[PDB]
Image: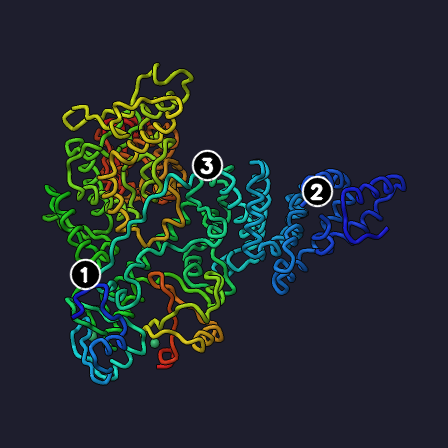
């Protein structure tokens, strides 16, 4: 059981080993709809570097539809300001390569290649509730 | 006698020779061949006083003045290249010397410089890297007030000159002019020098930023990310504030009043919707004056904030629609309050608290009020009436929440209030909603309250408004030169009146009745007593009030754009009463027109009124004796004909600013009836 608030695994791979099971074996519920994830979604949850949410010692993930939906709502709600990558580097005194930026549509962390694309196409990065976001390749093409 | 760098002594060599040969062209050759070179200047010296002596000697000759000007025009465009492409300052931190040398020239503000030389120099200077600006600003903060005034004036004249000289319109924005933008960035540099040069109190006055927890949805998304404990991130902070380590809010008293940095001509020309856009979305080719808030007047700022509020209200409306499309749930796009006239405080509390607990984001919707039993569309008049009722009810001494001072006519928190922290939260929320809906409220708080709302504790100096009887007494105690312990016999214990009039003894320090106040500890006692009266006596109530206010303003640019003195203006409105502007915007109904004899006589009378009669007239017609943000011209007063000549007094509808005026037969009768109405109301 994961009824200890502090000492339960956070990332799906860890939960796999903690339950002596593999990503190919495990079945999980989405934290909003409590519907079961498709295996494709489970993989993507691992790829998106997201955290397991726990209620009463039970683990929950998030499916694709819910994640996109709530992310889009959060964009509409806590948008702050948009900067160019160059400007952003100066505000944070670090190169964009190193700065933590996620996909605004699907939370997937952005690769330095995608970060470069933002600089190449003179596109801005959006601050939402104090965290920075951009658009990954799979969301700038749709 | 060619030389690569210059000094006072080297200059003197030529002063004498030029006088002796009755010539100036050699010295002009020299000065030109010097000051056209950035390197020569950077290498020449920091020797402020030498520079000052040199200028005081050289600028005495007209021929040499034109040479300085002509050298500066040549110098600056090259310096811009050095800073933009070669990062020269990162190779030689002495490069800043150049700008220090030039700025000590006293004649930069004469028109000859304003037309070309100073603009170019501003373009160069405004490109300095932040660390260099920080070095320069820290130096300027040691200058005399008149010198800050001179530098401020030097750029103010330039911004004024360029705004007046160029035709700006909705296609040619002030935001597209490099000269004004560069000048503004320079002026910003001066502004922070003024801030840092003032009195700054950072170690005894900070209060914690209390943020309302977001709705469960955003919480779950924050939990799904690694942000469970990272709820506190602050608003958009100015890079210079970061580099200097001092906020605009930290300076208790500047060298030059912040109001003098407001450039009214600029404010008359600036289009705020576009500026706010550029503030929100960074574009490489356009600037935003909101990044330079010191230059904007309260009207212009409020219009920016109003765009923020409206854009958010509209975003919440979009979210409402999106929720309805994906999950079928029907949410109200407005903050619809329904209340009973006999229970306004209770109904408003329960509703606003259920809303704050179920969804703290709802408080950011557009306010819409409905009195249970009444029928009308809330175009703001019903809301205004609701605010009047709430404010009147909350300040009634029978509720015991506030104490009213007859002397200052200001309200202050009752330390002895048993009432629940709910009511204090309600009044806090109401203030927030008023700013959010641009409605002036007849609330009368001393400056300390707006400082505490911004997160600064009230200091001894703030008692000067809230408790004059107290402030004066404490000031007297500080000014006394005898043995405080033997002469005043006061201890670290004070007396406070309960609701029932009983004197409650409060110990400022443990067993305070046994601890005497001595000359060495009196300043500490004053700090503690001030801290008790301004904080520790009301802290229970005030903390609730402040929470209520932040529930509406937590994400607003308010903390960045405004100061305590400007918050007051947003909530209560201005004390300046321009009746010419009121005449220009007044509308007429019932068959009156601007060309009606009675209307012309009305304006002759009203212009001849005293300021007190004018305040009474506004109170009568509008429900407040203050003018909205931007003056009386923003008040859409309507003079509506209330029948032919009669013995009746005029009447008013304060919720819509309508004056019901009979068509009197004479100017004297109009004056006498109007004076009587406004005096006896
Ligand atoms: Zn789901
Ligand atoms: Zn994506």
Q: Tell me whether circle 1 and circle 2 mark residues in contact (CB < 8 Å).
A: no
Q: Would residue B273 appear left or right of A24 to someone viewing this image? A: right
Question: Mark 2: which secondary structure?
Answer: helix
Residue at the image point whose x is 57% and y is 39% from the top: B142
Marks 3 and 1, the one that precedes in the sequence: 3
Residue located beneath label 1 in the image: B332
Please tell me whether mark 1 sits on a helix, a strand or a loop.
Answer: loop
Q: Chain of mark 3?
A: B
- Identified at 16% across, 47% down, the residue is B348
Residue B107, percent from left and from top: 67, 42
Q: How far across and how far down the image is residue B83, in percent?
A: 62, 60
In the drawing, what numbered circle is on residue B51? 2
- For image coordinates 28% across by 34% down, the residue present is B619
Q: CA distance from mark 3 to mark 2?
A: 30 Å
Mark 1 burial class by Cα count in 10 Å: few <14, some 14-19, many 20+: few
Q: CA distance from mark 3 to mark 1?
A: 46 Å
Bin the neighbour count of mark 3 within 10 Å (Cα to Cα): few under 14, some 14-19, many 20 and up. Answer: some
């Amino acid at each position: 059981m994961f009824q200890d608030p502090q000492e339960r695994p956070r990332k799906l791979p860890q939960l796999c080993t903690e339950l002596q099971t593999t990503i190919h074996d495990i079945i999980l519920e989405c934290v909003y709809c409590k519907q079961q994830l498709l295996r494709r979604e489970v993989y993507d949850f691992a790829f998106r570097d997201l955290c397991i949410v726990y209620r009463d010692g039970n683990p929950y993930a998030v499916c694709d539809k819910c994640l996109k939906f709530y992310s889009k709502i959060s964009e509409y709600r806590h948008y702050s300001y948009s900067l160019y990558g160059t400007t952003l580097e100066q505000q944070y005194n670090k190169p964009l390569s190193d700065l933590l930026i996620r996909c605004i549509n699907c939370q997937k962390p952005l690769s330095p290649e995608e970060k470069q694309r933002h600089l190449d196409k003179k596109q801005r990065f959006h601050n939402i509730r104090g965290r920075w976001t951009g658009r990954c390749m799979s969301c700038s093409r749709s | 006698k060619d030389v690569t760098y210059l000094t006072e002594e080297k200059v003197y060599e030529i002063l004498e020779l030029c006088r002796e040969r009755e010539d100036y062209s050699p010295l002009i050759r020299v000065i030109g061949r010097v000051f056209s070179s950035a390197e020569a200047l950077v290498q020449s010296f920091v020797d402020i006083d030498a520079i000052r002596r040199v200028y005081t000697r050289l600028l005495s000759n007209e021929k040499i003045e034109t040479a300085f000007l002509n050298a500066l025009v040549y110098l600056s465009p090259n310096v811009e290249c050095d800073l933009t492409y070669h990062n020269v300052y990162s190779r030689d931190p002495n490069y800043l010397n150049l700008f220090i040398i030039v700025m000590e020239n006293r004649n930069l503000h004469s028109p000859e410089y304003l037309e070309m030389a100073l603009p170019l120099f501003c373009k160069a200077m405004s490109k300095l890297p932040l660390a260099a600006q920080g070095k320069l600003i820290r130096l300027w903060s040691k200058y005399n007030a008149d010198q800050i005034r001179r530098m401020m004036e030097t750029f103010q004249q330039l911004i004024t000159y360029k705004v007046i000289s160029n035709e700006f319109n909705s296609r040619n924005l002030v935001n597209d002019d490099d000269a004004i933008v560069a000048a503004s960035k320079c002026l910003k540099m001066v502004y922070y020098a003024n801030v840092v040069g003032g009195e700054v109190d950072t170690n005894h006055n900070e209060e914690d930023d209390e943020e309302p927890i977001p709705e469960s949805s955003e919480l779950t998304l924050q939990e799904l990310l690694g942000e469970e404990r990272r709820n506190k991130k602050g608003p958009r902070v100015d890079p210079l504030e970061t580099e200097l380590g001092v906020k605009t809010l930290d300076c208790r008293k500047p060298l030059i009043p912040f109001e003098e940095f407001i450039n009214e001509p600029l404010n008359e020309v600036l289009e705020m919707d576009k500026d706010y856009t550029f503030f929100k979305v960074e574009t490489e080719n356009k600037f935003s004056f909101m990044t330079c808030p010191f230059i904007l007047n309260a009207v212009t700022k409020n219009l920016g904030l109003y765009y923020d509020n409206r854009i958010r209200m509209y975003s919440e409306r979009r979210i409402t629609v999106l929720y309805s499309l994906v999950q079928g749930q029907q949410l109200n796009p407005y903050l619809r309050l329904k209340v009973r006239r006999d229970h306004i405080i209770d109904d408003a509390l329960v509703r606003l608290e259920m809303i704050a607990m179920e969804n703290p984001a709802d408080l950011k919707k557009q306010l819409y009020v409905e009195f249970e039993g009444e029928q009308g569309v809330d175009e703001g008049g019903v809301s205004k009436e609701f605010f009047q009722l709430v404010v009147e009810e909350i300040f009634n001494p029978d509720i015991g929440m506030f104490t009213y001072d007859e002397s200052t006519k200001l309200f202050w928190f009752n330390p002895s209030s048993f009432e629940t922290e709910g009511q204090f939260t309600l009044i806090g929320i109401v203030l927030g909603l008023a700013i959010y809906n641009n409605c002036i409220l007849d609330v009368h708080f001393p400056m300390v309250v707006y400082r505490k709302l911004m997160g600064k504790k009230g200091t001894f100096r703030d008692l000067g408004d809230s408790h004059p009887v107290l402030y004066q007494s404490l000031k007297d105690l500080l000014e006394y030169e005898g043995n405080v312990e033997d002469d005043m016999m006061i201890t670290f214990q004070i007396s406070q009146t309960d609701l029932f009039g009983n004197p409650m003894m409060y110990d400022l320090k443990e067993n305070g009745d046994k601890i005497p106040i001595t000359n060495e500890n009196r300043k500490e006692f004053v700090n503690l007593y001030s801290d008790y009266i301004l904080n520790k006596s009301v802290e229970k109530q005030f903390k609730a009030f402040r929470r209520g206010f932040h529930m509406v303003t937590n994400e607003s640019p308010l903390k960045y754009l405004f100061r305590p003195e400007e918050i007051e203006l947003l909530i209560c409105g201005s004390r300046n009463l321009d009746f010419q502007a009121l005449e220009e915007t007044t509308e007429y109904d019932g068959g009156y027109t601007r060309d009606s004899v009675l209307i012309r006589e009305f304006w002759e009378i009203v212009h001849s009124f005293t300021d007190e009669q004018k305040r009474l007239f506004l109170q009568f017609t509008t429900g407040t004796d203050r003018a909205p943000v931007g003056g009386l011209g923003k008040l859409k007063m309507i003079i509506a004909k209330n029948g032919p000549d009669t013995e009746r007094l005029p009447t008013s509808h304060t919720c819509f600013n309508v004056l019901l005026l009979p068509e009197y037969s004479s100017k004297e009768k109009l004056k006498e009836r109007l004076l009587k109405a406004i005096t006896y109301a």
